[PDB]
Amino acid sequence: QPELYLMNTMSHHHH
Amino acid sequence: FGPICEIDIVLNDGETRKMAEMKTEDGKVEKHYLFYDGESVSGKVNLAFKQPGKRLEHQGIRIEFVGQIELFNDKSNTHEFVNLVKELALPGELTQSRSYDFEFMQVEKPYESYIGANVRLRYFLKVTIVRRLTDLVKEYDLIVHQLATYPDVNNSIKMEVGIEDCLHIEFEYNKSKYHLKDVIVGKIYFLLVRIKIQHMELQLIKKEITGIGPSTTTETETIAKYEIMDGAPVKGESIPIRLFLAGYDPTPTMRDVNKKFSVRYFLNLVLVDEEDRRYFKQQEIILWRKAPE
Amino acid sequence: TVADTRRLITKPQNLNDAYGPPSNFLEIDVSNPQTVGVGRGRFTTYEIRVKTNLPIFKLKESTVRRRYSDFEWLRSELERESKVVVPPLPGKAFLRQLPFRGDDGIFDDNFIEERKQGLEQFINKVAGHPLAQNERCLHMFLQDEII
Amino acid sequence: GSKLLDEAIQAVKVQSFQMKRCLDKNKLMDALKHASNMLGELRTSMLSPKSYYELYMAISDELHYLEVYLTDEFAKGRKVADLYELVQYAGNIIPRLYLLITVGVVYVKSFPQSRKDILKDLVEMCRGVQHPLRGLFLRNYLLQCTRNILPDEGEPTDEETTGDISDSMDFVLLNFAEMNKLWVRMQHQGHSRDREKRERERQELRILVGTNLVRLSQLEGVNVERYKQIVLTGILEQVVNCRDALAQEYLMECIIQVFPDEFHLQTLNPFLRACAELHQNVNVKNIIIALIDRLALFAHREDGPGIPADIKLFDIFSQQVATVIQSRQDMPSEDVVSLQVSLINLAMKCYPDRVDYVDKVLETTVEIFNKLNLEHIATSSAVSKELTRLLKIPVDTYNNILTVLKLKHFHPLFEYFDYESRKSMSCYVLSNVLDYNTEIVSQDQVDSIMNLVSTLIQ
Ligand SMILES: [Zn+2]
């Protein structure tokens, strides 16, 4: 019933 | 009539020794004597004779210290990892009450006592009076805790996770390894926010992995749900975490105990948006039992 | 010490982020029901009016006219490629199209009202979904004036 | 419906009854479970700001019975161990943080050594509540609970206490910046057709944000140099950068009202430079007028220092009001004249002696009317309303009406009036010269009486 979404890792990406 | 004889075990340090508690099925809390790897177990086996006049023919009396692992409530799957024997009497008779001394020198107890869903690890003394057709048997349970010290290395957990072009966050927990009454100090930091977040929570999750290879069963239990944010943040917003583990009385992490089972803890971060969609990341944390000074 | 007041150090929020408008604005209104045609080929249409500040959508404001089949077309397009468990539509009402009912059938005011509200319920759940925003069928449905 | 509010206030009364029941029996942890259930009612989103405000006040009044229970208990030596930690176990954040704040202030009173850290903790841990309404009311509860216990200068000299005035300023300035953030954030939540309802809702809640500024003025240790360097610098940074007319207008007026006139005189050019940077929909006229009005009541108050000679009010306000009007894109001409009235009013009340100032306003007013390529100004037009009210002030306020006639630029303004208003105004001036008897008129003033007659008849 509830939509789960695994959060992906982010590689070598800066802010 | 009842029984002819009743077996009672009494440890030599039965007044001074500290006890401990175990949560069993449907909320029950047993209390047994606490032991540590290397400690000697010694005491008395006390046979109380109940039917005066009668006599008890036996082919030996012994006492055993036993540590064993039980899987899926199945007697045929029980494996003893520690067994020690002391013979207390040769084949004979008993007409009256009598007591016997026993001492197990420096007993190895490599694992911590555990009661779970598909696994029990328990220690006990077992006295057996051997008879012609049915033995008189008396078990006497014990808790064993396993201690550790502060780890050499204890790196903080820090990571950027997200949903590309929706939500980018950077979470941080102050340690990888927390003792049983430790505190998760951490923070969530928002780098990009293009969804409407209702609330965020931190969950402590306990996994009990049983079996070998493809024969693997995993029982999951969510021990804590801790809300850490209420409302929709924007970028540059920081959110503090302070989650006290004392409030949830967890067990230590137990990794490939006797190559039969594992118990592992996870911090599952969960954000929930306005349409009840749920975004998560899971991170293992080692829990450990701290040696008191 | 009487209280554990431990926290990690935080970076001060830049004032443009603190006070600037949030980047998650998305509302879609299904409104104003109208009958198109006469006699046998009559059908209802609704004005799908969007407002947004998300960079994935091409127009910040848009207004288009849609049909109940256009909603059914969208849901079938998303079910095949998107891998998003799509929410339900308000329902194909076949037995309302049958003749000589005790109401105005598919053009009943209470029917159109409830249908209309169910379309708005549907389209907001679908258009807010991350994986659904990548599909070309959503932008085609919401912002191109004909599919 | 409006039932939600009553149902909630009912449930509060059930739980706060069972709370005090447990507090009478001395079963604290059982009381904190009901306190938590009571505080659960503040988690809702379904109430309006008014309804929610009522629910808050109900729960706030019950939380005081818990706060006083703890404070007495702790003062009598029977201090509950780990209470700061224990209340944080609550799974929901709103009950948790209301409880944490409540126990926090008890710890500050009972353990003065922890004061700096606990206050700094409470302000920081409130970052958990990002929802505008609930966040505002949380950070308001923080500010009211901590009213008496913040650091200050006139304090008991207990040398185991922690934190000074600098900590108090950072505490309140931060809570201010967070509440103003949440409050401006209310402008963009919800549906786009309720724009007028939102601005109504925000207006109701303005006092929650403004109480932070009220709290800063109440700190004895906030002297004029700290106001210059820390407090106003802090407030003005949030004000100009929030880019929100509703907040900017409210907050700049709120500064004027809350802080004393000693502080305003040292910070005039900063406060007026800020006015030029505000949003175009801000009524800048009303800000400047409110300030001048306040400085006028300071000039006429005796048993006080008055206005220092080095602070040249007229040169500052004349030059800045000009700069402020320049910054506006489309200021109505009536408003420009409404400001000339207050520049007269300022010069009249702050410098009665200096007539040349009052004439310089009228001289500059002429330059405004001359610069504007104006069509004939009717008596019904708002410009004429103000120019009439402008000219009447010297005539009405001065003791000796001869002094009005000596003004060089008083009469040239009559040119710009309607035919009806020249007759009305000339009559009004000349009528006053008879209503109070006339002494002999000097050379310049004989001229001005005949010039008044020439506008009356023709
Ligand atoms: Zn990123």
Image (cartoon, grey):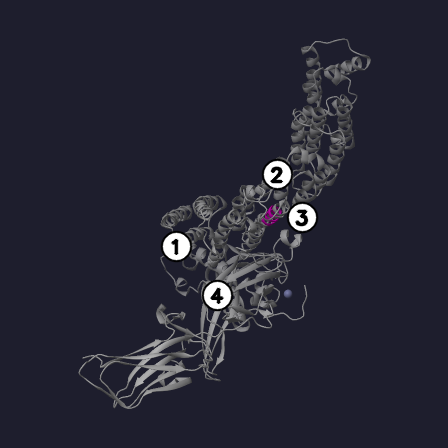
Q: What element carries label 1?
A: helix
From where the camera sits, is residue B274 visible? Answer: no
Q: Is residue B131 left or right of residue B32?
A: left
- Closer to the eye: label 4 or 2: 2
Query: For the point 46% across and 55% down, which residue is it?
Result: D81
- Disc 3 under 8 Å from ligand 1? The reply is no
* Chain letter belonging to callout 1: D
Residue C122's tag is: none
- Disc 2 under 8 Å from ligand 1? The reply is no
Which mark is first along the chain, 2 or 1? 1
Q: What element carries label 3?
A: helix
Q: Do labels 4 and 2 share a chain?
A: no
Q: Report the amino acid beneath label 2.
A: Glu
Q: Report the amino acid beneath label 3.
A: Asn
From where the camera sits, is residue C29 visible? Answer: yes
Q: In this view, does D372 lie to the left or right of D104?
A: right
Crowd tier of the residue under label 1, counting other residues whose Cα lies within 10 Å: few below 14, some 14–19, many 20 or above: some
Q: Report the amino acid beneath label 1.
A: Asp
- Closer to the eye: label 3 or 2: 2
Q: Does the magenta stretch include residue D262?
A: no
Q: Return the residue nearer the eye: D384 or D136.
A: D136
The residues tagged by marks 4 and 2 sit, at their Cα atoms, a distance apart of: 61 Å
Q: In this view, does D47 lie above or below D429?
A: below
Magenta stretch bounds:
D171-178
Tell which residue pokes out farthest to the right in this image.
Answer: D443
Reading the image, the residue beneath label 2 is: D220
Q: Are marks 1 and 2 on the same chain?
A: yes
* Mark 1 touches mark 2? (CB < 8 Å): no
Q: What element carries label 2?
A: loop
Q: Is residue D383 above or below residue D191?
A: above
Q: Are marks 3 and 2 on the same chain?
A: yes
Residue C87's tag is: 4
